[PDB]
Amino acid sequence: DVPTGCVTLKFVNNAKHINMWDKTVLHYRKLYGGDEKEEWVIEKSGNDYKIRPRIYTEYLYAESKTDDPGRAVKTLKEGTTDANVWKVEQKMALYWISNVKYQECLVISGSDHVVTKKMDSCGDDLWEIQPVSNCLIVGK
């Protein structure tokens, strides 16, 4: 079904991969839609999944309130969170991703924001999850 391990995360409609900032701000790392093939790790978490970049042990999560461009998604450097578990579901060769806590689809916006958005269905906002052989997950 969903590949676990090292993957690339590419939003189909935009051709944008999830990229991250080089330097952590406060307790979080900012993300944006970019064109570089950033490597991420999908880990099984119960019936659902957690997501982290290959080189940092920081878990993808969704913020607690919705902003103008949508509910911001970033990785958690310091602290704890309840919104770091992701549903990842196959639709033929493509996937849609949804935050479990808030039931909102992960998406890259037209302005390159990485956000979740409540939709009747995530099935029109699909991701390309291409596995990356030679997967070196950094610990700490």
Image (cartoon, rainbow, N blue to C red):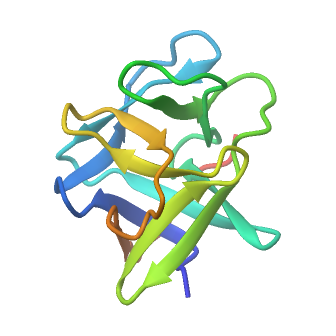
- The C terminus: image quadrant: top right
Which corner quadrant of the image does residue 89 belong to?
A: bottom right
| Above or below 26: residue 110 | below
Q: Is residue 83 visible?
A: yes
Q: Residue at x 52, y 32 (%)?
A: 74
Residue 65 at x, y percent in the picture: 61, 22
- 13 left or right, relative to 64: left
x and y percentages locating residue 93 in the rendered image? 35, 86
11 sits left or right of 14 in the view: right
Query: At 38% from the left edge and 72% from the top edge, which residue is drawn?
Result: 132
* Percent position of residue 55, x then y: 51, 45
Work out whether residue 133 or residue 84 is closer to the camera in this orientation and state it: 84
- Which residue shows up at 53% across the image and 24% down it? 66
In this picture, residue 130 sits left or right of residue 34: right
The residue under the point 27% across, 39% down is: 109
Q: Farthest residue toward the front? A: 120
Front in this rendered view, residue 51 or 71: 71
